[PDB]
Length: 36
Length: 110
Image (tube, rainbow over all chains, first blue to last red; front, side, top):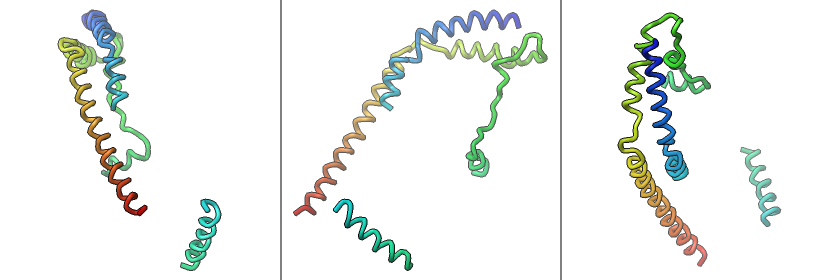
């Protein structure tokens, strides 16, 4: 469970960094969603 | 008269009228079947170990391998271009229908 607490911390911080950087294409998503 | 003759004729027409799957359809009643609300919560102190490893580690590793960027925005904008080719085609048909519709009315007018 502590090993996973390490993974949740390390992986989720990378996921949050990857997600915020990606931003769900949030400008490309609006570009794509407003088109569809 | 867009207010008298239509109302008059409607009453005359009115007077002549006075004279004369199983699972899917059931779910439609308005309740979606519940899914596995287990993986997210769990508990360190609480019960079950598999949930820790049989739920969170392997999926997080698959997530971190899946969560990506290598291609990044290039893969997204490539699909955005396809959507523009799909959209213009519809409006071209809107025109073709618009022309033939006005063309038929044009013949009636004469």
